[PDB]
């Protein structure tokens, strides 16, 4: 059975994010930006589009904004990648202005959400990885920094969310999407510890493709266990 | 016929026109005035009991756009405190608005006409700012037009964000930011303007001297501000 | 002649004095105790149930001045996490203050004598911070003296800003940042000792021994801290 696994991992590693995983992410995030505008969503979206778009972009690339800040790199940075900004703006356009509010309505249907919900955990596992990597690039010896920046990209979307609100002058602790994503932060810490530990090389043995597999496996295990344990109540 | 002519003259002298030291004293003046007004009934006893804290905030607001521009571009937010000239001039105005004899400087700025010129002057400077924002940005990311747009807009409208973080840090909240509700259009003005300049620099499809456009946009920043001064 | 030598010898030894680890275990010690208290009644449950959050909240407060300093200067704010020996030591004090057996380390720090001892050392530690802030600012921009001062003051008495933003992100507003009234003399003392050291390095307007002047401030920060315990 092993073979097939190392084939799973070797492929996983090669798996690109653009554009399906991205659009899954951008989709879930912006649908939330909308959902949180409370009843005001409809009116605000129509009279303050830029202000609305900006809030959506902050949440789509929140992990980057956060890492950059942590790393002394220019926060504006995420706006160089025209590819991503475009795609997200499109997804942004649809969630707020799609005809017959279709796209919004389709994502909200149970089976679909779940696909997305999973796809996203793959994109997260990916971010946790690229964080620890970039971290170890600039600071190969400082493991803590690697683990933080990793956990930063894996779960720091909440912080950017809080900051955006405090600036819009609105407090909204519905910060409980699922009361479960709290698993996200701990998961991202261990997930990052490992990759951080593995890159140093000093103490663990097994192929990256195989370990990264198990962590993406877990992320998906839980984000499902959050979807499936919510539904029974 | 005659209208096309007159366009070039203003630009030349406009572009030659240094904001310093009069536009800076206009701007500083208004900003530090506002810092004093939002200080409410307290303002009076605060300025005297905590001159430094009073100063910093005033400093923060005079150069707010700078502090933001830097942060966004990774640059040291401390940098504005380097230009010793700007800080000295500003601090003077600061000193006046809060401690002028018979609080004269403050009042003279209050009258409908004066306060209206200080404001029209501030509009040119703001444009001056959106210009420098787009340029410095384009200089670093010659082809990341969004970034340039954002930074220019930040440069021309970002005072609000700094204002907010300062209050948060001081544990106080006043959503009454929009003294006028044009400033939500002001930012929009800055956004369209900034992205106009971002286009010029790209060098794609555009015919008009640089001295011609800076003046055309000023007409709009002044027009929106004037449309805000006439009504109420 | 007879006693002119006793004071000159103290400046050389203070210069020889390391901060690690007896001063740090004081500073980290105090800082982390405050983190604990502020969690209020829930402090107990929260520390057991959310050890990580609690830890990061601590580290933020132990190295606050660094974070603020880095941020200001344009440097990577995550930087102070590279110093393993510190995070290591600081984490121990953290472990102790929160989960010590019979909670001894915490109690010991509570007695008026010990809290007093620690209080002073930390003050030496501050002196230290103010210094390097002025230094490192001067290293990069030795002519911009304001920056050297803000950065010195930030470094010296800026943990309050970090505390504020930490609460804002935690969704709590415990504005009673006011433990003692001294942390109000703390920021000003830091502002002076900053401008004094920023002057020294300029050397342009006065000559004085580096070990005497540094020794005087260290005593002055301790003076104000003593006045808090001996006067009230
Ligand atoms: C002067 C400058 C001074 C410079 C100081 C910088 C020093 C640097 C330190 C590096 C720290 C990086 C660690 C990142 C860990 C982290 O994730 O932060 C925690 C702790 O935050 C608190 O609640 C607050 C608890 C206190 C501790 C953390 C906050 C400190 C952060 C620094 C930001 C400073 C502000 C700038 C938040 O994580 P969480 O569990 O509270 O929030 C979750 C989490 O983010 C989930 O991943 C997320 O779900 P997904 O969208 O599916 O990913 C949910 O997001 P939503 O709001 O959209 O539903 C959130 O509900
Ligand atoms: C951790 C690392 C994470 C950090 C990474 C983030 C990197 C992001 C890059 C994008 C930055 C683009 C900024 C350009 C837009 C901008 O400036 O914002 C606009 C609208 O949007 C909002 O923020 C209003 C609220 C709507 C939602 C947007 C929130 C943006 C938040 C991000 C804050 C990032 C900074 C931290 C604010 O403009 P406004 O209409 O809200 O406020 C007015 C307006 O600025 C007026 O021009 C101004 O009067 P003037 O003196 O005549 O200029 C008023 O100020 P005063 O009361 O002192 O007179 C303001 O009160
Ligand atoms: C786009 C970005 C926007 C760009 C903004 C760049 C601005 C640049 C230059 C500013 C540089 C000046 C920094 C030096 C000031 C400084 O040190 O802060 C002062 C004044 O605070 C303000 O009014 C704070 C005034 C607000 C401005 C600075 C904040 C920048 C950081 C956060 C972002 C927010 C932006 C605003 C604090 O004032 P304090 O007397 O209340 O604080 C004390 C003091 O720190 C004591 O040492 C300490 O007691 P100890 O235990 O003995 O050490 C107490 O801390 P704890 O109770 O937690 O132990 C504090 O309670
Ligand atoms: C070397 C690796 C170490 C780096 C790891 C990064 C640190 C992890 C931070 C996540 O910790 C979070 O802290 C929050 C505090 O803001 C908790 O809020 C929770 O608990 C609070 C009370 O303490 C409630 O007010 C909130 O509603 C509730 O969500 C949240 O659950 C917890 O996940
Ligand atoms: Ca509140």
Image: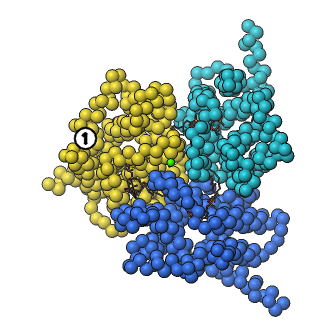
Chain colours: A yellow, B cyan, C blue
The residue drawn where x is 42% and y is 40% is A60
Q: Quadrant of ligand 2?
A: top right
In-front residue for pair C90/B56: B56
Query: Can the viewer see residue B104 in this picture?
Result: yes
**In this view, B74 is above or below B218:** below
Dot 1 surroundings within 10 Å: few (below 14), some, or many (20 or more)? some
Residue B97 picture quarter: top right
**In this view, C41 is above or below B78:** below
In-front residue for pair C101/C87: C101
The residue drawn where x is 73% and y is 65% is C192
Quarter of the image that includes the N terminus of chain C: bottom right
| Place of residue A3 in the rendered image (x, y in percent of width and height, measured from the top left) | 18, 54
Identify residue for label 1. A114
Query: Is disc 1 placed on a helix, strand or loop?
Result: helix
The residue drawn where x is 55% and y is 62% is C64
Q: Chain of mark 1?
A: A
**In this view, B35 is above or below B193:** below
In-front residue for pair C121/B196: C121
């Amino acid at each position: 059975d092993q073979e097939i696994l190392l084939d799973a991992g070797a492929q996983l590693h090669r798996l690109k994010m653009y554009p399906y995983f991205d659009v899954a992410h951008y989709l879930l995030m912006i649908i939330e930006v909308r959902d949180d505008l409370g009843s005001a969503a409809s009116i605000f979206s129509r009279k303050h589009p830029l202000s609305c778009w900006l809030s959506s972009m902050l949440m789509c690339f929140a992990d980057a904004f956060l890492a950059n800040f942590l790393l002394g790199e220019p926060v504006i940075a995420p706006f160089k990648r025209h590819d991503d900004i475009i795609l997200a703006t499109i997804i942004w356009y649809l969630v707020f202005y799609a005809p017959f509010d279709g796209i919004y309505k389709i994502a909200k249907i149970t089976p679909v959400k779940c696909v997305l919900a999973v796809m996203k955990e793959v994109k997260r596992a990916y971010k946790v990885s690229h964080g620890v990597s970039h971290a170890a690039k600039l600071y190969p010896n400082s493991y803590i920094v690697q683990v933080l920046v990793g956990t930063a990209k894996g779960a720091g979307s909440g912080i950017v969310r809080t900051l955006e609100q405090l600036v819009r002058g609105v407090w909204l602790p519905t910060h409980n999407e699922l009361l479960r994503p709290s698993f996200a932060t701990k998961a991202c810490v261990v997930a990052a510890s490992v990759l951080a530990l593995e890159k140093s090389g000093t103490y663990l043995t097994a192929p990256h493709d195989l370990v990264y597999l198990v962590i993406v496996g877990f992320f998906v295990y839980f984000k499902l266990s959050a979807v499936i344990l919510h539904v029974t109540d």
